[PDB]
Amino acid sequence: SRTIGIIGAPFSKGQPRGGVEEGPTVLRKAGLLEKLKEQECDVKDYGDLPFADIPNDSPFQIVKNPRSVGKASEQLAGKVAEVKKNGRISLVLGGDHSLAIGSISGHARVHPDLGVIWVDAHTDINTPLTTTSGNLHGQPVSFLLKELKGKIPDVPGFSWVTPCISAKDIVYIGLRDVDPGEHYILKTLGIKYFSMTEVDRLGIGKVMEETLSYLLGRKKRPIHLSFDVDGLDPSFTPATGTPVVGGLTYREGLYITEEIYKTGLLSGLDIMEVNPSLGKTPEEVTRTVNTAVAITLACFGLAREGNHKPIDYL
Amino acid sequence: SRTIGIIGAPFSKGQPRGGVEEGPTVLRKAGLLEKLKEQECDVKDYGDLPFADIPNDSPFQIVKNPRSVGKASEQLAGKVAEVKKNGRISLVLGGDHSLAIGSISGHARVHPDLGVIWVDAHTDINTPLTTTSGNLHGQPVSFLLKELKGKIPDVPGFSWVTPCISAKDIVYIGLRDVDPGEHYILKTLGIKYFSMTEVDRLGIGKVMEETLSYLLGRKKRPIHLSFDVDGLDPSFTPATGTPVVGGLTYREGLYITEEIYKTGLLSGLDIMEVNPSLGKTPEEVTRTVNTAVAITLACFGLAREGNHKPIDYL
Amino acid sequence: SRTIGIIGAPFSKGQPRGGVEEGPTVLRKAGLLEKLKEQECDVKDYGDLPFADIPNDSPFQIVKNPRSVGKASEQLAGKVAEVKKNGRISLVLGGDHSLAIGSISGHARVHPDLGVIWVDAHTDINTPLTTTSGNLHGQPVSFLLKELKGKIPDVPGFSWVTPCISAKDIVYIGLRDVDPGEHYILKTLGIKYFSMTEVDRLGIGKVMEETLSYLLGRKKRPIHLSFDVDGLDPSFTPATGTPVVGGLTYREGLYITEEIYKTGLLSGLDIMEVNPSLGKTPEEVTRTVNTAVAITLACFGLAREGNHKPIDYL
Ligand SMILES: N[C@@H](CCCC[B-](O)(O)O)C(=O)O
Ligand SMILES: N[C@@H](CCCC[B-](O)(O)O)C(=O)O
Ligand SMILES: N[C@@H](CCCC[B-](O)(O)O)C(=O)O
Ligand SMILES: [Mn+2]
Ligand SMILES: [Mn+2]
Ligand SMILES: [Mn+2]
Ligand SMILES: [Mn+2]
Ligand SMILES: [Mn+2]
Ligand SMILES: [Mn+2]
């Protein structure tokens, strides 16, 4: 089977807007665990992590709330490593994308051979020195990459981090708002990506074929899908902090996640950047949450062609 | 030429909402016959069928309004067989999709070799025993399939039905809300389908190439297109009873119907499930009707690249 | 480098609605020149052309405002030829599409070997005798084509025109509302086109590969892109005079223009038919202008994957 361990991560200090803290609540209120159970799934809820307040947390140079973000990911890393030890797929409900530092680190403690698929409008690979916003949700990949060891200063809250993935172990899908220093890093390190230009050229079918052949061609290994809902067009996921037009369609989102399910190798999942307070109407909220739920159920086997139990229904 | 015989089928008892009865009226009011005439076409209006009320029509087990639905399709079968005998393409304006039992049966009385293309979010292949809703618009394909003879109980109103197509003679396009028993039937009988996952993988161009090669590869034969407007995304066809997100685009709808026109083998057409009373605004209504008209004109030769008469326009 | 010369062409008499005169103003107010400068670009503003009023300009047969439209294009031709002589890419901000008569003519005075890519819902190839509207924005290609010399009467205001491109030197992309005489001309002269049916069949990636191989396969030559914002779906560009559903997506627009940038051969650009007074809300206006700006920045190197200077950002 495909057993799941849910971790709520109601955390926002990777970016300015507090409302991403409500992500785990609204996803749960939408029926996510029940819907997973209705499907094939063995679901264990590990609850919502209690992130304690750090009142003294002044910027490190440009970088904001560093101790809060570092501690939150340190905590999340421990929890993810626990559910992996318990032989379940970690499903992290965010919260802002800085949490991927903890989610991927904890996962790699148990499965050092993982490969990452990063669905996002953004590369999230600024370093604490290339960042212009100082927002740690725009930096998580730089903390994770072994090649960028030497380029990450000693940021308070992160001394526990050990880079765990190499540039050859991640694929981006959905890119359309990449900062110049980020583009430099991508080209310098030879990281594999499918920007929206590539999705337009190739179609999502060939994008997935190529993604999965690149990560799993040599040998089967665990897959970590880090899904920023702003990877999808804001006509599907408007209640998010950094929307960018010309995104992946609803259909393309489901296709990506259906194909990853079918590898049988999904090992960790992040559903990040849902911020209900940013919808301009209550329907923009429902739209966003419903889409996030649909993407999540596809990761665990819900197929558009249909599903049945191995019984004779006639 | 390509002569057409219009049949209005203002019938709703295959499902709960009465407003699909207005389908033939609003399609006609939108200028459909005049627009067909403006095009290449020889159009004969056979009028709207008068469906008489059946006051005593209690459910058969789960199954609702069985005698009303059976009689309506029996009537429609006769009428379609008439216009086929008169050497015209039957164009059935619905009405709910239970009418396809009559439309395809009547057609097959004259052209037993037909092939069916079924454009829908749904497979409509529940049997009277697998159905959970008891709504006959979700069952028509099971009454038509020769393989499912033995699995259809003797439902009052349907003793006149003789299954007329085999599992190898239908192709589905657009599927995204298939019940478990339906998915079992699809896999058991080896029915050809292009769910939205397949349309995403392949593109609509390859979907059509493959559809038409599957049905017409061995030999040319008449094609019956049964078109449920909920096959298209509800952003194009919102005024319908069972909308499902992530549908075929307007463009994909026109492409399907342009390609079928170009085979020269269109023999019967169903335009089903238009329900103006379900639009939330008068523009949702116009949107839905206009899209249904556009799909219909493409079936009879309107091409996006343009059209001209065999005259010298210079 | 890729130096640009901006020409504002605030002209509307090719069609009935005056508000396309505001196109150059709103594009400039949206930050277009500054955004180009932020990118790689060497931008020289040649200002807005002053089109003088012609009070005595009665129709020529069907054809409206002929002397106004002819004079405006004569003026624009001179200006475009100037900026080409100055070794810059002419960027014409319209204004209605009748201006392409001047823009392409002026360009060809300096680069007689150019090839044209015409992005539009419409072919704009009516002659003064096949037109039914008499609106010159629907006629510019017929004045430009050497093969249609003999079929263009002597229209007042156009005696200065010399047809400068052959039928083999233009490719259309986006067609979906082509008049019968226009379709006759397309088929008679064997003009290359990708209607929306072809874009649906092939995908925009293969459309661009085929466009560019057709125009540049034999030898490199300058490219003139004439971009009517109604080529894009009205969900992206609603503030325009002749919207047509089922258009190119935002993504497809950016892909077309990214691919043309990458040839290194863009030589002239037209951004036509933006009419802010036709948006039904202030957001429809911003939507339309923002999309036109995005298409324009892609023509000059803005890439969705990102951009960086040849510096070490680490
Ligand atoms: N590159 C910008 C945007 C980051 C957006 C972060 B994300 O993808 O997690 O939403 C920044 O560094 O601040
Ligand atoms: N499978 C559901 C939905 C049927 C919808 C029917 B249709 O496709 O014609 O709109 C049911 O059996 O009730
Ligand atoms: N074919 C119609 C429509 C022309 C629309 C012009 B255009 O593409 O520049 O917006 C006419 O001749 O009037
Ligand atoms: Mn993002
Ligand atoms: Mn992100
Ligand atoms: Mn349906
Ligand atoms: Mn149906
Ligand atoms: Mn146009
Ligand atoms: Mn035009």
Image (tube, coloured by chain):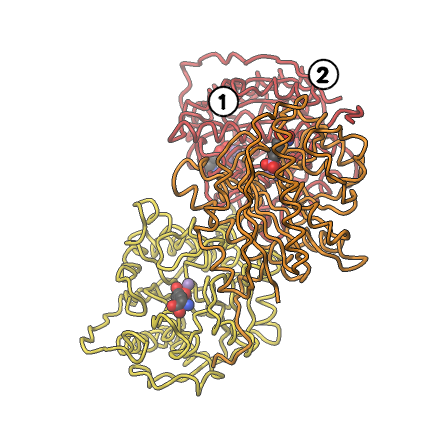
Chain colours: A orange, B yellow, C red
- Image quarter (top left, top right, bottom left or bottom right) of the C terminus of chain C: top right
Count residues near mark 2 (Cα–Cα under 10 Å), then give few for <14, some for 14-19, many for 20+: some
> x, y (%) of residue A227?
60, 46
Is the residue indicated by label 1 positioned so its CB lies within 8 Å of ligand 3? no
Is the residue indicated by label 2 positioned so its CB lies within 8 Å of ligand 9? no
- Amino acid type assigned to the residue bearing label 2 in the image: Lys
From the viewer's perspective, is the residue at label 2 or at label 1 nearer? 1
Q: Chain of mark 1?
A: C
Q: Is residue A124 left or right of residue B76?
A: right
> x, y (%) of residue C52?
48, 12
Find disc 1 in the rendering and name its residue.
C23
Residue C178 visible to an observer of this rendering: no
Q: Which of the marked residues, 2 or 1, is nearer the chain's N terminus? A: 1
- Amino acid type assigned to the residue bearing label 1 in the image: Gly
> x, y (%) of residue B64?
29, 74
- Image quarter (top left, top right, bottom left or bottom right) of the N terminus of chain C: top right
Find disc 2 in the rendering and name its residue.
C85
